[PDB]
Image (cartoon, rainbow, N blue to C red):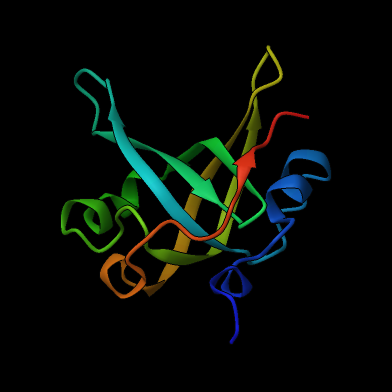
Length: 123
């Protein structure tokens, strides 16, 4: 039947990393979430995300969305649709993608596994 990767926006990560058009609404799977060091500032969560074809490790959650992580709605394996995001390219070429607005379409436990065979984007 229909493959699980059919749920994900295959090619969105390449598009974001090349064209940088933020007027798209890609559906992505969360692979991992990690808090980073922030000192006296609110926690920031870095995400490893998948579009089914690629993963990218440089996604960041806007802190306004921290409750999604802290109340355990946005977690490893869940599928989200991104509705607003910002691209911030660093001096070394790394392109950080900041997720501002999103919908959790399908919970981690309704998915259950990492979907497909995505490979890290590095081109």
